[PDB]
Image (cartoon, rainbow over all chains, first blue to last red; front, side, top):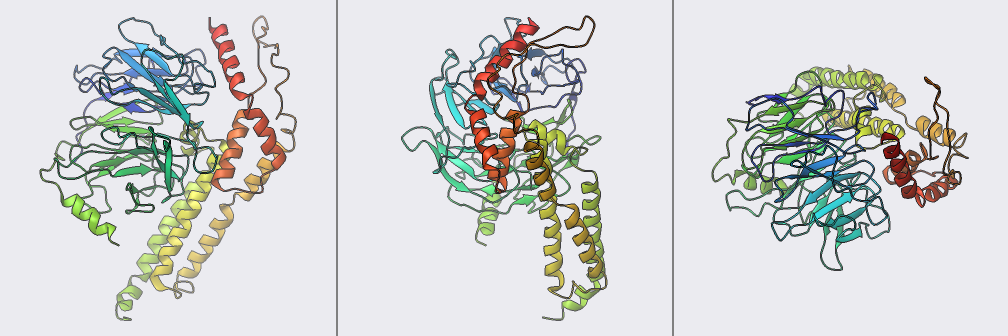
Length: 358
Length: 198
């Protein structure tokens, strides 16, 4: 069972565009961000036009319109900035929009210097809390750059990302684990997914684990079972149609869950109910599932209207619903409803450990 | 235990036909090649060249094809080959292997790049170039000379890390020279575009 709620779409700004990454309100509740892509059929329009919506207000208009010059390859909210919107681009500059200024252009654009990114940033993110935060931009070039949300003309802390060999690490949708232990996992271009540190001389790339050959599209981490498990588990996504569960100590671990007749594009599993991961396809199917109940099948899955290549999906934080980003500019909103967080749900840990023994 | 093999022989029919269903479905997917399929848009969104997206998509279908072949290899071991319908499965697979070939694309890539991109590589000197744009009034704009070269750099990196060939070293070093001057050009191009918009 999947509770298909309302949808968000506006032809005024989703006119034959590609829905890029998403994010829910990391500060507010259920008011999400939608990064888009350029539509070369409309060259007069801005390339990257981000948009937001408000599920808690129950309306249809894209509440805010924001648009830099280039195509926004990534976007999300800002940590403890209830007026700001951070953003990655295709060119390499990192933008910064504001809502209260009513300026449909970002007010603080990262330069295009070598010290900054001159390659698209697929994953730019805030990290800790009030005093524990920063802004880490990681372009596909292979550089990380810490930035304050105040100073943006120069990266606060910045270094590259290379393996033991001096070859580049074409990152794609990295993710910090729970707690910001600075050991963020990095979805590389294809295979060689890495764990990478930030503080110490050992910062950067820790080790390579390869369990799939198709080019990576996403990664995610999660939290506690209700203070039962460590939950450092992180699942990935790739173009080989398979999704592998990983560990911080394995190299070719846990069963690579494969969805056939579909090009996997993203995974993100809500820490609420320790295992409820949702993958997507290049056909219009949301085949999400829990590993405790099922084993290798989508639990309460659904397909999507028409055949949209579902680009990105995000669980509604601290609760349950699903944001859906397609290859076509349209946002769909589903919900589990009946797939409530099971209490004392350690069945999954016993399950994954029993599978891990073979 | 050749006792399970009896019901296996019974469902050999259903197993081989269902696997034929899936392989012909793959045939339908390949026949709707990469520039047509949604893999083109998605692969371009994640910034993959058409060469790279095409050959990656093709090798993924190759892997899924041999994956089904591995399934049938598990079905009977060796009897599935010269089976009642496995003899046709083998044919479907062989023709589908010939369909799924990327050396043609690799050759066309190295070809085109060595047919006309021999001079496209180091076009860094003439930084600015005026234009002509046949429209009403026939205006002229400003343009820097780095349009496909940057994608060629990405192409080489993708082939090298992805599969790795005996990639033309001259093109690799010319790509290296384009890389070491590329960010400058990005900044210039965006400045020009913002200038035009203003």
